[PDB]
Length: 220
Length: 213
Image 1: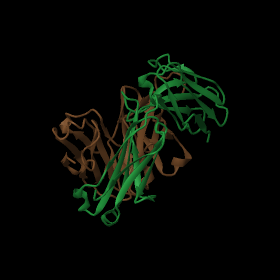
Image 2: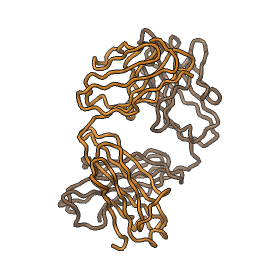
Image 3: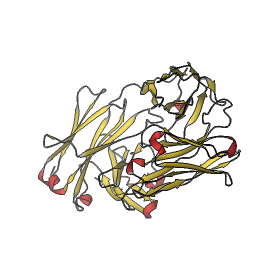
Image 4: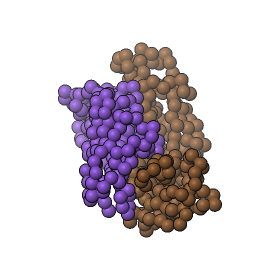
């Protein structure tokens, strides 16, 4: 039994999207399908349900106007369509369902999530700049280094250090959207300062959407 | 159009303590309520349905109660894997509204951050903008204040923050603030300092550099 949703999308404002969600393992037409929205770092919010047997939908007023949910029993997949896209529609969209509850419309089964981003921004790889302290003396025996990963779009990026060799003490921060319309984050790592720069700390950044692997040797 | 208000908004309990979230419905809702658990990245999980029925597989720690307008979820003895956001949901009527969620987090001894400051790379100054970066890593609790000052002048609209999820081993948080300004502004001014205020600090810690050193 699984719900598999369609892939992340990047959409201009005023466009329309149709996310799908396909069901293996059970009879779609015997149960309800619900879609739910989760705005970046906000709560879940119920959009609407559909009865695949009937075609009968109910919505939340918030969402009635601009969202249409439909279901195709021939492919056992349920679709969700927002029209008139808008930056605030950027959120993860979930199909969900209940069929082993045995007493209620509570949802025991959910999809991966499907990320919709609405932006006028164009696809663009990141520029990478090293974060090291001024000098040098420095700490001890403890210093922080890092990587400013700035001006890229869309998400996501993969940061790593020393091609994976270094994982302890490393924190890569939740990306942040700037007024550019572009994303900027940074990755940092705590290290022992006596060991610096005996060891080099390279920092590998990967932005698949713009085919971009880049690399910074970081040094104070 | 039924509104599910849950409280607290954030709960911090020691490993093995009890955890009480509860939920208030705007309108009598009978037994028709579920709770869910969500973790970063993952889709949600159903824990209780019909106000007090464990979905099979969910362990005994979790139990729900109440009927009508006042409902509660209990976690007998919190464990490492129970850190998540906890949501309340009504299936009584027309729009099946969720609550806003309660963040449940491991209580830890207090710890102040270690503050570090980074000047901009010459590599970036070529493009004509300067990002100064202040990093407070490994602190608890999350509540932290951070002010930028350029030559003693409180900066206001020109910086942005980001915060990690609580750490698996440490149970701690790290935060970075980034001050953006132009190459001109950066080259005219001289002292760049971030100043950090936090429970574990007995009074604010300033980290600062002067451009020309």
